[PDB]
Each structure stands twice: as C-alpha cells, then as structure tokens.
RNA sequence: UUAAUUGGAUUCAACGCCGGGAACCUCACCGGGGGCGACGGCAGGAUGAAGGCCAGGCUGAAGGUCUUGCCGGACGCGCCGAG
RNA sequence: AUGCCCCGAAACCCCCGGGCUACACGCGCGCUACAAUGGGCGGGACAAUGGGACCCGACCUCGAAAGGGGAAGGGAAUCCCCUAAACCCGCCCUCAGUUCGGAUCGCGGGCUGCAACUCGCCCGCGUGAAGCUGGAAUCCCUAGUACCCGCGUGUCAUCAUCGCGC
C-alpha cells in the first residue's frame, strides 16, 4: 500500500482549519481512507527587544511572538483523490507540502 | 485500569492489574530508589489503603518530566487514582481526602512566567 | 543502603520520620494543644496551600514547621553577637531534602542522647522556650509610651521555633562542629531550662523589659 | 619522621604525601598525586615514614619527568625556552626562568613587558576603580 | 651569548621557517602557518632588500601584528602606533614576539588634582 | 533479575570486582595522570577509578543501547567553577571513555554499530543479569520485600 | 580605494534595512531589521500581543 | 590622564543605559595620506583624458606622488550659483 | 521623516593604524569570595523557552582539550543541539585562612576571524590575592511566592558575571 503525507502549515488558525475541512470532505467524498488531521505542535517564535529608543528610561522590554500551526494528513493512495487536491483553493497564508510514503 | 497523574511537569501513566503485589517505577522496584524521601512519597498512598490491597494488585507506572521529587509525587498521584478506580471503595477515597486534599484532586499550580528587570533570578526579582 | 531500606519499612505503620510514633507524645501547656498538630503522616512535607489559608499553618505537622524554620535561617538585619549568620555554602533555601536529612540525623542524635522520644523533648523545649509577655508603643497626644502586652500563642510558638533555629544556626556558623550537632545541642539545652541556650536566653530577655514596662 | 626533607625542601611528615609534596614551590596537588602514582606508593600514606630511597626516587622523578610515565604536558613549561623540550620547573629554577622571561619581555619592550615594568593588567583587565 | 630553544642567532638563521616556527609559541607558529597578508610579504621583501643593501630608505611600517623573525635582527625600523612611526631596533633577543608590543599606543597616565 | 531490579551503585560496585579478573580491561599508561573529566578540578583519589569507569559504561550500554563517545562525555560531564564567574557545566574528556569502549569491544561485551554507537552483546547481557540475579538474591534475605 | 571593505562577519556585516543603524539587528529567519524599527513594523507583520 | 578613552544620559525619572556583543569596521575621538565639486554660467575641447601601465625615489603602502614611455578613444580641468 | 543654521574638495568620501577596555580614589548594579552542607571517588531519578543548511551535527577514530580525518539524518513532533541542574546514597579527607577560593605571572596546545600583547575564550601546568561575617546606615518581596540550582534562544565568529525565556 501507499499513503500520502500532507503537511498543511499556516499562521492563521481559521484558514488552516478550512483547508483541513476541505481535505476531509474531499476524502470522504472520494471514498478513501484518510487518517484524520493530526495537528503537530504549534511553533511560537519569540523575539525580545527593549522599547526605549534612546539609552534612557528604566529597563523595559517586550516579547513579540509568531504562532504558526501545522497539520498532517495521511491519505491512502487514490489517484482520483490525488488529482482533486490540486484544485484546493490554498489561501495565501496556507502552504501545502505533499509527500508519498510506501 | 489506566490512571493519570499531573504535577508541575511530571506526567505519570499508571496501569493497575491483579498481581502478587509487585509495583515498579519505570521498571524499577519501589524499595530500591536511592533518594529516601522520594521513596517515602511513593510509599505513602498505599500505606493507609491497607496491606491487603498492597499485596492484592500489581501496578506499573511510567513517569516523565519534573524532578525525582516531581516524578515521585506524580507516581503517588497515579497510584492514588488507581487504588480508588480499581477498588471503587468510597471509604478509601474519604480517608485519602482526610489525609490529604490533593491525592485525587491534585495541585494545578505551576511556575509563573519570568518578566523584564532581572528576569533570570525570577519573575519578581528587580534591581536594587 | 540497608539502614535506608530499614527506615523505609519501619514506618509502614503510619509513623513520622521513620520511628517515634506520636501517640506517646503529649502536650502540657493548654495554649499549644489546639495549635500543635500531631496528625499521623510518614513525611512532614505537604506542599499545602497554607499560605492561601489565613490560619491554615496550624494544620501542618509540627516538625514540618521546624524544618521550615530551619530552612529560613541565613542572613538578615538580625545581628546578634556581631555575626552574619549566612550560608553561602549550599544555602538551605528551597533545599528541603537537606532540611529532611539533616533534621533526621539531628533527631537521631537526640534519641541516642536522651534515650527517650525526641519529639517529647522537642515539645518540652518548645513549651520552655515560649515567652509570656512583650511590649508595644502607643501614643495619645503624640507622646509615645510603652505598654506591656501578652503574646498570642501562635506567635509564641513562631518565636520559639524561629529562635531555636537561629540559636542552632549561629552555633553552627563559622564553627568546627556540624549543623545537626548544633541543633541537637540547642534543643536539649532548651528542654530543661538552661540559660546557655540562646533560645531560653532570648525568651528570658524578651519576657523581661516588658516586666518593667507595665 | 617529623621533618622529612626532599629536594632540599623540608616537609612535615604528619601530612599525607600528596599534600606533603605540595609544600615545595614546584609541586602542586595534581602534580603531587601523579608523582605519587609514578612512585606507586599510596598517596594517602603519611610522609613521616618516607625512607631516603623513596626521597631519591621522587628527586630523580623530578629530574626527568617525561620518562617516568608522566606525559609531556603535565609540566608547567613544556617546550622550554632554551632547550625546546618538556621539563618541569621547581623552586629556584622556576625563579630564574620567570625572571629571564620578565627581562626578555622588558628588553624587547613589549606591551606585556611595558605593563611588567610598572605593574598593570597584561591580559585586558580594567583598573578604573579596581586594583 | 644568546640562546633560544638551544639555538643561537645564526643557528636559527640557517634553517627554514618550518622548524623555526616550531620553536615559536602557538599564537605565532599558527599565524605563520596560516600565511602572511599581501602587505606583510611586501614589508618582508623591503627588509630583505635593505639587509642586502638595495633598499636604503629608512623603513617605516604599520604592521603591528608582524612577528619578529631572526632574519630581521640587526636593523632599525619605524612602527606605527597611530600618530607617528616610533623607531625600534631588532636585537637577537626580539625573537618570538610581535612588533606591535613595542610601540606605546597609550601615553603614560598620571594623576592631577581632583575636581 | 535484570539490571532494572537492583540498585545501580551496588551493581557497579559488584561488576567492578568481577571485571578486575579479566585482563582485557586494564587502564592505559596515561590513565592515572589525567583527571577523569575536563570539568574536574582534581584527579580521582583512589587508583581503581578506571575500572569503575568501564563498569559504568557497560551498564549504560545495557540500558541506553547504541551510544557514542560524545554522549558519554555529556553524561560524565560535570559542574566546574570558572573563577570569579559562576559555576557552569562542561563535558568530560573523550579519550578516557574512548579507550574504555575500545577495550570493552576487544572484550566482546559490546559491539559497534556504525552511525549509532555501541550496543550490548548477548554475552554482556548474560554477565550483567547473572550479576543482577546474584545481587538480588543477596538483598532478598536482608529485604524480603524484593522477593515479590 | 574609495570602497569599504566587505564584511561577512561581526556587527559591521549587518546594517538595518530601514534605519541603517549598525548596532542591534535581529536576524531570526532573516528580518534584517533594527530593534527600534521593530515597533512600527510588528503589528503589520501579523505579530499579536498576548 | 592621553591622540583617544567620542558623545549622550542626572536623584525618584543617569550609571550590566544608548552598546540588543569595539582586534579593520563599529567611529560619532586622534595622526597621517588619497579622491572626486553633481547640474548649470565663465573657460578648455578631437590640440588628444579625466582611466589604468610597468623599473623605481617619496609613500606604512598604492601610477596616490614624481623621472621614465605610452594608449583607450572620448568630453572632461578649474572659479561662482548650486551641490 | 523633520524646520533653522554651518561646511562644502572641508565638517564630503575613502585607506592605514591607535583608542574606544586607559587610572593615585569614589559611584550603581551584578559575579566570585569569606567552608564542613563541605574538597574528592563511583552510582541515580530526573525538564523546557526554543535553535538548527557554509547550520545542528549524531556516529567512527587521533589528541588531556579546544580541535584534526570521514559522515548518517534533519528546510523540522520522526535527526541533532542534549547534558539538565538542585539533590541522595557506599566511602576517604576532619576545621585550618586549609583538603575553600582563584586574581595574578610565564609556558604548551586548540579555536575563530586578514589580524586577538593593546584586542577574546578554552584544555592544563609551578602558580593561586584579600577574605577567619563587615560600623552607623540602607535595598527588595508577600504563594509555588521569595530564595537555591540549572538550561537554551536573541544581540554573536570571539568576547556578558549582560539580558530574556523556561
């Protein structure tokens, strides 16, 4: 057997969930065993910076963070099911990387 | 029967089955753990429960995270939940509550985030 | 590790530390009976929310309170005999496991010294090291004046415990002998009313002054 | 033996040998332990029962350290300035070598030598409020 | 007489740079191993020519990290510290140390009356 | 009984005296003159420290399976003072444990898996669980609760 | 002769995009931005305060 | 104090602050050297560069500088406004 | 961004070097250091902020070590960083300015980067300073909090005992 691992990565929660919903309904319409969406741990990239532009004032800093979420979908080999994922409307904030695994 | 234990960062997964009385901590016997206070914390939940139930069941616990204090206390928590779920004895839960409120409720306290102005020593540690 | 396993199996019958089951222990002074906890527990380490309870420190085991007062002892504005009681050498703060082992060995020393229950000696010393009067300042018309006061028993046991701990710690500090020895000497002195104890001497000096400030 | 003299430097026999050898300007705790291992004697064993044959054993150990099993690097001045080989430096010889190096840095007039001419930080240490 | 690792001035001179660097410290031998910059080689050519007698100019320089070699012994060169090219003379004892150690970049700091 | 069912310190102490007999495990000529770790401020006190190292390593190979030199440096690393700076962690020296692992391989107690480290052979497991069974039998009479 | 030497290393190898200051430049994933410049650009960058 | 320890910051509300990283750089400080004034007005122009070129003396040093001998084929020296 | 004013082959640009760390004292805040918990030997339970393509670098071998020769996997739940530390036990040393602490000197080696004596760190060596608890005075905090202990990321090749987050 063969299964495609689909990585869907986005900063926006709702667009990622929408793409996951689209893949879900695609898989359940195409009659393909699709291991449900597995959200991998969300990455929180954090950068700290002092707020005083000049050298004066008490030591005051802020931590600015980016939260990026990722989902993994294992979908069984169905070339009919694999032709239609290429028609998925991918928002600009979402990216999809599909690999094949025996 | 599977049981949980959450303490600080110590997560304990315990599984209790009928057996000779063997209890093992990540595959290690309870009596051999070199820190004595950790051994006593692990031992406490099964003392008051009774010696009969100490000899009646076998429990295997895998505890990850926290320190050896945290791991011992999470094993204690997991054993506490396992005893009540296995026996289902209200009196055991009641006397556990008398001995301690957190043996089935647990302590959801954690470490607070650190903050600017000498964060390293702590959140509230500031300059003189 | 054989005495360790022996001390691990002895207290299977709901016993504090490893031995000295507390049924034999007694409270003499009426003020400390409803404020000293003789509850049966293997360990004096509850991690409880007594800081979240106004008067929830009384429910803690007495030796747990003693372990606390031991681990609160180094460095302050508290200057006696011109000495900085400071532990720059593995400070006891937050290291409650040292504050468990050291106390266990100290209580062992008491057991082999007195031959009796060391908890009985401890309670006798607490009763003998608890003062009975103090002072306060009150002002009418801006003229201050000192008034004698009588302590609440909770603050009495607080000062007794802290004072015993400070006496032992000062004995230990910058000294050849160890801290367990210091505690073991101090509490046995306090048990039988020797002024050589810093605890009893401090009790006497704080009980006085208030004598004349009436 | 209350007083045991080795390499012309007296030591108290009450101290353990690994500690007894450290009294010499030119043996440390580590060096004392490894020369004790060279001699094969227990470093714990006190220095008061040191027969003179073991004293000479230690003397000739210090005479040529590399051949006795101590590697080439445990010495303080490997690749010695005037031989190019590895030799350990003890007491008076250390004094002469250090003075020769000081006079070397001075006669070249190095910044290191310049700071050695008056007593200042050679390796970047600061003295605004310090020293 | 002069001694360095068991070799005198001429005994050092007759040999190539490989063992000559093996006699030098780590900071000097390693830097020599990693090669010389375009302006170090040019200055070496200048001083070799001067020792031959071709380069009769009083030679000034700025390369402070220039490691003195025995071949440079017996010549006077002017090294830059930031303002001027202070004169220095190379004797046999200069071997194994940088040239930039030999120019005061900071004048003497003495103390006057406090404010 | 396995290595799990016995205290680690007692198992190491037992294994060292058995490894004493076999001649393959032997300290090199340079062992006593180098302290056990880069971080260490001192040489080890006793002269048997080499065997305790080897006896330690095998136990790790019994439990942690394929292991390399660097991870052994990290586990055997310790806390060193940096002077007026605070105390910080550092890894131990690699040559000592490399010689130890090489001698162990020459003893056959472990086998090299390239790209992963060294794992424990059937013979090493037999030696170690025989030792553990003897230790557990020894501790059973003194502590009957280990019979369970 | 009139060209600054290339620098792949050190502080001089980084000169901020916006303000051009040679000092604090965070390069997490290659922002290539000054610390004082990050305040005007963070909210538009999808950063959100929590 | 220095050539420089660049300068800023004044008790709360300056002093592990600008520096959230000084061996060239950082440089805002000092010593020394080289090079162009854009676009115009006045002036030269192909009458031959302003770009580089060896051997070298001054240059730390580099056709930068100059004796040396020259091309590459073309708009570029310079004063004022204004850069 | 930014008015006004100044200079305009300098106050423009560039090259080199020096300094940016210089000191008879004081200042603010941190790190170490003023022992017997201990110095040392072996063993053990133990995390996370996160980072990773001239990067993490597993892993093999040479070197005390920095690092030298090769290279698996990883554009990140799959591989590495990476070990956590505090701490307990079997045991030696038994209280002194030492079995503490290391400044400081010179030597050897490794790194980075054109180059680190000015102007780095580390693996070590003879080396190892004051310090045997500090005066009036005075700083901070109020529940998992204070404190102890450790860790990595950002600034970065090096440099902080910086700082942040855990």
Image (cartoon, coloured by chain):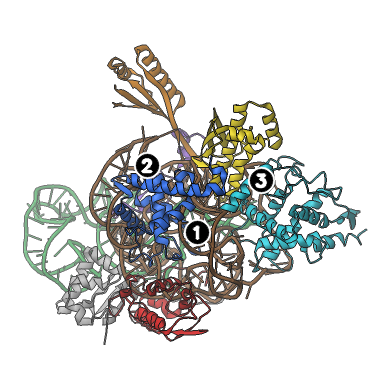
Chain colours: A orange, B yellow, C cyan, D red, F blue, G purple, H green, I brown
Image height of F124 relative to I23, above or below: above
- Mark in the foreground, 1 or 2: 1
Residue closest to the far front: F141
Expressed as whole percent of the image width and height from the top left, the position of residue F2 reads 44, 43
Disc 1 versus disc 2: distance between alpha carbons?
34 Å
Say left or right for I45 vs A30. Answer: right
Give neighbour class at mark 3: few <14, some 14-19, many 20+ (Cα, 10 Å): many
Image height of E6 relative to B17, above or below: below
Chain of the residue under the numbered disc 1 shown in the image: F
Which disc is residue G30 wearing? 2
Front residue (pair I99, I116): I99
Which residue, given by chain and number where applicable, does mark 1 sit on? F87
User: Disc 1 on helix, strand or loop?
Assistant: strand
Whether residue C102 is visible: yes
Disc 2 versus disc 3: distance between alpha carbons?
62 Å
Picture residue at 66% right of the left edge, 65% below the top: C173
Asked if badge 1 and badge 2 are on a common chain, one would say: no
Instruction: Name the image quarter holding residue F16.
Output: bottom left
- Mark in the foreground, 2 or 3: 3
Image height of E113 relative to G33, above or below: below
Which residue, given by chain and number where applicable, does mark 3 sit on? C11
User: Disc 3 on helix, strand or loop?
Assistant: helix
Expressed as whole percent of the image width and height from the top left, the position of residue G10 reads 36, 54
């Amino acid at each position: 057997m063969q299964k495609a691992r689909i990585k869907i990565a986005s900063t926006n929660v709702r667009s990622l969930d929408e793409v996951a919903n689209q893949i879900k309904q695609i898989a359940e319409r195409t009659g393909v065993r699709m291991s449900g969406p597995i959200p991998l741990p969300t990455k929180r990239i954090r950068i700290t910076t002092r707020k005083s532009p000049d050298g004066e004032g008490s030591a005051t800093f802020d931590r600015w963070e980016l939260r990026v979420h990722k989902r993994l979908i294992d979908i069984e080999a169905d070339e009919r099911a694999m032709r239609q994922i290429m028609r998925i409307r991918v928002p600009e904030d979402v990216t999809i990387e599909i690999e094949l695994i025996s | 029967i599977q049981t949980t234990g959450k303490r600080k960062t110590a997560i304990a997964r315990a599984v209790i089955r009928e057996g000779k009385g063997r209890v093992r901590i990540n595959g290690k016997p309870v009596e051999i753990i070199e820190p004595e206070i950790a051994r006593f914390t692990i031992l406490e939940p099964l003392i008051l429960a009774g010696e009969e139930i100490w000899n009646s069941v076998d429990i295997d616990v895998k505890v990850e995270g926290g320190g050896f204090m945290g791991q011992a206390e999470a094993a204690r928590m997991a054993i506490a939940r396992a005893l009540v779920e296995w026996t289902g004895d209200m009196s055991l839960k009641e006397k556990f509550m008398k001995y301690d409120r957190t043996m089935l409720v647990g302590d959801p306290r954690r470490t607070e985030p650190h903050k600017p102005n000498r964060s390293t020593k702590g959140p509230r540690a500031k300059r003189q | 590790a054989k005495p360790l396993n022996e001390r691990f199996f002895i207290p299977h019958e709901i016993k504090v530390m490893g031995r000295w089951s507390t049924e034999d222990v007694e409270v003499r002074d009426p003020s400390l009976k409803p404020y000293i906890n003789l509850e049966p527990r293997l360990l004096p380490h509850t991690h409880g929310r007594h800081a979240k309870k106004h008067f929830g420190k009384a429910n803690v085991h007495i030796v747990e309170r003693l372990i606390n007062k031991i681990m609160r002892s180094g460095g302050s504005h508290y200057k006696v005999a011109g000495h900085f009681m400071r532990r720059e050498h593995r400070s006891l703060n937050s290291k409650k496991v040292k504050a468990y082992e050291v106390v266990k060995e100290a209580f062992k020393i008491i057991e082999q010294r007195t031959g009796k229950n060391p908890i009985q000696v401890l309670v006798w010393a607490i009763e003998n090291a608890a003062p009975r009067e103090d002072t306060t300042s009150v002002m009418f018309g801006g003229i201050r004046y000192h008034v004698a006061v009588d302590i609440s028993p909770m603050r009495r046991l607080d000062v007794a415990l802290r004072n015993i701990a400070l006496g032992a710690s000062a004995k230990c500090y910058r000294n050849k002998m160890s801290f367990a020895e210091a505690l073991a000497e101090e509490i046995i002195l306090a048990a039988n009313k020797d002024p050589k104890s810093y605890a009893y001497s401090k009790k006497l000096e704080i009980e006085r002054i208030a004598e004349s400030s009436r | 033996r209350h007083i045991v003299r080795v390499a012309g430097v007296d030591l108290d026999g009450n101290k353990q040998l690994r500690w007894a050898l450290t009294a010499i300007k030119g043996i440390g705790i580590n060096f004392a332990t490894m020369v004790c291992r060279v001699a094969g004697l227990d470093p714990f064993m006190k220095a008061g029962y040191l027969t003179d044959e073991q004293v000479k054993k230690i003397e000739e150990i210090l005479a040529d350290p590399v051949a006795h099993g101590i590697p080439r690097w445990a010495v303080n001045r490997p690749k010695d300035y005037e031989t190019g080989r590895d030799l350990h430096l003890i007491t008076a010889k250390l004094d002469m070598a250090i003075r020769e190096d000081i006079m070397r840095l001075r006669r070249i007039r190095a910044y290191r030598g310049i700071r050695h001419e008056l007593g200042l930080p050679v390796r970047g240490q600061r003295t605004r409020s310090n020293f | 007489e002069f001694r360095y690792r068991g070799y005198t001035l001429e005994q050092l001179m007759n040999m190539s740079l490989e063992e000559l660097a093996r006699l030098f410290p780590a900071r000097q031998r390693r830097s020599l191993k990693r090669g010389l910059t375009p302006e170090q080689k040019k200055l070496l050519r200048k001083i070799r020519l001067a020792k031959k007698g071709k380069y009769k100019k009083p030679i000034r320089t700025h390369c402070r990290d220039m490691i003195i070699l025995p071949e440079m012994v017996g010549l006077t060169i002017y090294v830059h510290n930031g303002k001027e090219f202070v004169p220095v003379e190379i004797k046999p004892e200069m071997i194994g140390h940088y040239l930039g150690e030999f120019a005061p970049t900071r004048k003497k700091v003495e103390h006057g009356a406090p404010g | 009984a396995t290595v799990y069912d016995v205290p680690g310190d007692l198992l190491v102490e037992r294994v060292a005296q058995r490894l004493k007999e076999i001649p393959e495990i032997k300290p090199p000529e340079w062992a006593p003159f180098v302290k056990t770790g880069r971080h260490k401020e001192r040489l080890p006190e006793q002269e048997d420290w080499w065997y305790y190292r080897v006896a330690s390593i095998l136990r790790r190979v019994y439990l942690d399976g394929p292991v390399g030199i660097e991870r052994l440096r990290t586990y055997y690393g310790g806390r060193k003072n940096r002077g007026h700076a605070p105390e910080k962690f550092y890894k131990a020296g690699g040559s000592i444990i490399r010689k130890a692992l090489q001698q162990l391989e020459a003893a056959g107690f472990v086998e090299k898996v390239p790209g992963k480290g060294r794992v424990i052979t059937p013979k090493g497991r037999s030696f170690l669980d025989k030792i553990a069974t003897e230790l557990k039998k020894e501790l059973e009479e003194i502590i009957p609760e280990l019979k369970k | 002769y009139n060209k600054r030497k290339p620098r792949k290393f050190g502080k001089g190898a980084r000169r901020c995009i916006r303000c051009g200051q040679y000092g604090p430049i965070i390069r997490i994933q290659g922002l290539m931005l000054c610390r004082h410049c990050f305040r005007e650009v963070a909210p538009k960058l999808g950063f959100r305060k929590y």
